[PDB]
Amino acid sequence: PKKRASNGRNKKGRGHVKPVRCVNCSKSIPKDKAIKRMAIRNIVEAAAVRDLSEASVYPEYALPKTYNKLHYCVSCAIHARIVRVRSREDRKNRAPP
Amino acid sequence: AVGKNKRLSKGKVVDPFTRKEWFDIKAPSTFENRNVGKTLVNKSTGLKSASDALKGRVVEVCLADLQGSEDHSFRKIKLRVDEVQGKNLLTNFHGMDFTTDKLRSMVRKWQTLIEANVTVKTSDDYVLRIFAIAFTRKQANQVKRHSYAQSSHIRAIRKVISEILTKEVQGSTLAQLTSKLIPEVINKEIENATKDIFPLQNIHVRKVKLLKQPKFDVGALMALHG
Amino acid sequence: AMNPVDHPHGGGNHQHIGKASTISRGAVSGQKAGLIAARRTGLLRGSQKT
Amino acid sequence: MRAKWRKKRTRRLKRKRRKVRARSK
Amino acid sequence: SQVFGVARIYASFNDTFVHVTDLSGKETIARVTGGMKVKADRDESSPYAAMLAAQDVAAKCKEVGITAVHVKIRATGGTRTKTPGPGGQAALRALARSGLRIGRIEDVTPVPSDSTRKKGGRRGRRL
Amino acid sequence: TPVTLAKVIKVLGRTGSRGGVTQVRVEFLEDTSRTIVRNVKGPVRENDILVLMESEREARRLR
RNA sequence: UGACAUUGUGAAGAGACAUAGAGGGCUACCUUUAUAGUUUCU
RNA sequence: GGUGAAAUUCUUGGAUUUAUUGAAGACUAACUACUGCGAAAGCAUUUGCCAAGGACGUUUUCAUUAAUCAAGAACGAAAGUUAGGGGAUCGAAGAUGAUCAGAUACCGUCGUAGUCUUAACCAUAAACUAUGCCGACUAGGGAUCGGGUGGUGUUUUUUUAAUGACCCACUCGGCACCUUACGAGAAAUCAAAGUCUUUGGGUUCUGGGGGGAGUAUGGUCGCAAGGCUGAAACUUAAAGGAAUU
RNA sequence: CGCGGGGUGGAGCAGCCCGGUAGCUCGUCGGGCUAGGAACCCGAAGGUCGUCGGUUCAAAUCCGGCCCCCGCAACCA
RNA sequence: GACCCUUAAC
């Protein structure tokens, strides 16, 4: 039977959406169907921050971050636990946890 | 893997720091902080003539530690060596670009990204490709989530942007442009021109690429420091 | 299809070159028949960075 | 077996039948 | 005043390049990778080899006259993974702990606007 | 290399294939406020003194 | 392919002649200079 | 370098790595969405040019010119096929390593053919919303894309002398969106899959147990690959759908 | 009816820089894995080396006979 | 990382 009203993707009114390559396995996945997560991370991993700051030549250094839109295929999203299998009722919750 | 290289010599040394001597590299008067660092060259051996081993050299420095202000932290300047005066060499402007984190930080969803590039010629006979980036912004009191532009705002915005970058750089020397890019007055002037199209926050000028320079004209470079 | 008097390729009880048809650049006249100073041979596959 | 490959197997069979019939036609 | 170099850390998977240059970048001093601090290929990518390489890099550069380094960290990028490997933090961490001054950290991983084509095929790495 | 002496301040939890080791947060005996997170093979508890054959390592997990 | 010959000036750490550190499980290839003087890799 | 771990491989002849005038080809990231356009296939850098289009608005015009459609026609992803140009990248075919009983697979490294222009062909995809099109009616509620209407609403050059961008209320059209919901359904579920034994708005196409079998004695199109059309003998008591445990 | 190689456990190879009185793999057997098969792990057995005759420095490798596996030449009137 | 199979015998 039909599992999802959206067919596991976000494509109503298009027909075709260009693929993106998974960042784990390089699988071709439609962009509307990928599991994109945006990674904003401090560049010093938050455990060496004081060591880096105390070794810094500038006071109150801004400590920039890295920005990366990470795209996953469904197989790699499930395996890396980016998403998890959900019950039939609560598959309908679009709101992020 | 220290001892696994199967073959590196089928046949079966001088420390170069001794051979290398530090040279002073300096910024023009268009930037307030003059001394920016030190470079390395091998000795003055007849085959190499270290003076010409120095002339084609570019060092990328932050505008913050080139102007002593954390408000310039997100801009980096490429400075190109031009000639050597006895271990006291002197550079000219070579190119400017944005630091990676700033450009990534300004790009967010639920707004429109408006990029505009121009290849206008500086009156000093310098040819520059100047890139500008702007973002449509939420209006104060706006309830809509996304504040997107309508693709004809974007054409009009790009048009008024490109006219500004063309007019300003065409009619200014290369040094004058660098001294007007520092106070960011180009970004402000674009804000006033596009205010009647879309609110358009974050209107910075990203990379300033130098494409080709005129004849060296040793007097022009010495004009900055004399 | 010639006789050996006429061509380096001539002769034989079958029509065949017999020796490699790639000929050195330093070969002399009368010898330079075939593929002269050929860097390669066979059907050209892929590109040559041209 | 997978219908994709049974379709492929039949197509190879059809190709052989065309060839074996061609040598008589 | 200050004499600055560029730490220029390159943290891939299975290797991390911590290697300091001058301000121009055209003069390298102490190019030490974590591949020559461990015996096994698998054991490279660990932060230990990166810190060992960085420890040797600061030692070889504190003896040259480079007191401070600006940091230019980099993942493989391009078409490949684009995320820094496990040794990137340790290489950066061990540089600062080593008594070497640090300033102006940047992530300079090469990112394409529309890359060429990823490896692995259309079905990807299946394993 | 002169070894260092260290005192635990927090215990994180058991880790490893069979839980045979534990993550602990540890404070240096000299020049405190220098935190470190180490894996301990045997049974450990609060305010226990830890010896480190090397200092500048931090293993956040073990799997 | 090399040498010599028709091959007409200078410069550069001239494998320069006697008294000289190191890197290697006081020890004769490895940037060297203080004492008249024709030659370099090119 | 590469991996689960390796190995194939490159490294005096300097690999990998660092850093401005560099020959190429492809792709258009991030912005990018339960967003837009197109008949679908499909379409994402800038600018110029060229024709086109829906929606809106209209106290403009014609006046039934319409709906759906055998035959017939245009377009039709990818792969593939002739032909000259380009060939960076990746990479059907084609050799190492693990499996060992192999591994001519999955994983490494390479690597030919393969995504531009044609008389160009081919005409197929889970070409999917597995929902033919046109029309009417039947519940709720917000949001969004266009376009209009009303609010001396808020904010904006030379600051409160053309406007724009926001905010509320409507409205037309569109992409959609929250329920085992009146109704429908075998159920899954459904804003149509309702208005259907209280059975009829118009119309096109298709199916009649499973297999043999989309298999031609045939025909037709195609360079070919193949497309379209399409049985019978024979053999079966099931095959199948949606739930439940 | 000429010229050459080769014959070692059931099978395939080690004595061919003249000598470890015979070793290494597959197969077989025993045990262990597993709820039996397989795959895997740990052990064991197996041929006086085709036969006969020659130096007697561990000689049968290298010598001379017969058998067997084969291979090349078997033409020009 | 590797992991093939399973009654004709009521």
Image (spheres, coloured by chain):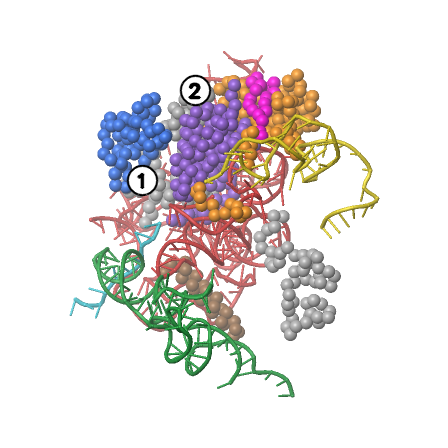
Chain colours: B orange, D brown, E purple, F blue, G yellow, H red, I green, J cyan
H227 to the left or right of F3: right
E52 to the left or right of B77: left
Q: Is residue B25 magenta?
A: yes
Residue H44 to residue B125: above or below: below
Q: Nearer the viewer, residue G26 or C5?
A: G26
Is residue B66 in sight in this rendering?
yes
Image x and y of residue E116, in percent: 52, 43
**Quadrant where the image shows the C terminus of chain B:** top right
In the rendered structure, find residue B203 and report the number of the disc placed on it: none
Image x and y of residue F47, in percent: 24, 26
In this rendering, the count of numbered labels is: 2
Residue C40 to residue A71: above or below: below
Residue type for callout 2: Glu
Determine which residue is flagged by label 2: A60
Where is residue A41, by image quadrant? Answer: top left
Q: Nearer the viewer, mark 2 or mark 1?
A: 1
G6 to the left or right of H230: right
Residue at x 61% of width, y 48% of height: C49
Is residue A29 in sight in this rendering?
no
Residue at x 31% of width, y 37% of height: F62
Q: Magenta part of the protein: which range?
A: B19-38
Residue type for callout 1: Arg
Q: Residues within 10 Å of mark 1 (few under 14, many from 20)?
A: few
Residue at x 58% of width, y 27% of height: B21
Residue at x 60% of width, y 59% of height: C42
Determine which residue is flagged by label 1: F63
Q: What element carries label 2?
A: loop
